[PDB]
Amino acid sequence: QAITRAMADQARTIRIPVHMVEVINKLGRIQRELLQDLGREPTPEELAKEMDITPEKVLEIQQYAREPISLDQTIGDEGDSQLGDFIE
DNA sequence: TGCATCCGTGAGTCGGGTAATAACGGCCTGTACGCGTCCGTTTCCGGCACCCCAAATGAACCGTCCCTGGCTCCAAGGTGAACTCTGGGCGACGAGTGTT
């Protein structure tokens, strides 16, 4: 319990409430189970059927789950300049 | 007391974006939203107290911008004659020519 609560409260650059992290992890887990079972990836409507909630909220959860990237990671094929040198 | 052993700077110039996990009820509250009701406002229907206001309805009316009246005093239309061409009419004279 302590480890999972701390993961939810501290693992992400943008804090996500545990009530939303739980649904994100559950969605990912059962979606990978569905992919393994069915042989293809599950579509958002199919995943919403298991979430017992609407595909709009499924998509909102999906776009919420994304994490930021570093402004200083090298973007070029070689190491020449940082991503921060491309942002207006 | 060297002595290996890290250990800390290079090394120039103007195509984009790639992922994981057991987690699950149950209670609280909190800020935002959703109901029902009541009161200040405000905005007009038609009323005056009358405010009167006024363009439209009778005058003159006098100067003036139109009519009628007569009068000229002149310059244009009517009345002459000639003449210098303008044109036709008259006449004579001369060689190229119809003919046996």
Image (cartoon, coloured by chain):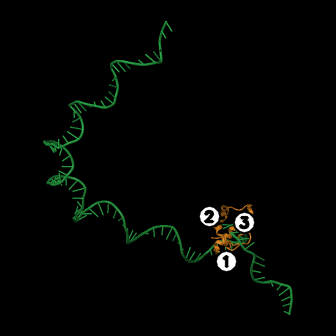
Chain colours: A orange, B green
Q: Residue at x 66, y 65 (%)?
A: A51
User: Please, what is the three-letter code of the amino acid marked with disc 2?
Assistant: Glu
Mark 1 and mark 2 in contact (Cβ < 8 Å)?
A: no
Up/down of A82 relative to B90, above or below: below
Do the residues indicated by labels 1 and 3 lie within the same chain of the protein?
Answer: yes
From where the camera sits, is residue A8 visible?
A: yes
User: Which quadrant of the figure contains the C terminus of chain A?
Assistant: bottom right
Residue B100 point in image, percent of width and height: 49, 6
Rendered image quadrant of residue A44: bottom right
Q: Secondary structure at mark 1?
A: helix
The dot on residue A32 is 3
Residue A47 located left or right of residue B73: right
Q: Secondary structure at mark 3?
A: helix
Image depth: mark 1 or mark 3 in front: 1
From where the camera sits, is residue A68 visible?
A: no
Label 2 resides on the chain identified as A
According to the picture, the residue beneath numbered tag 2 turns out to be A56
Q: Residues within 10 Å of mark 3 (few under 14, many from 20)?
A: some
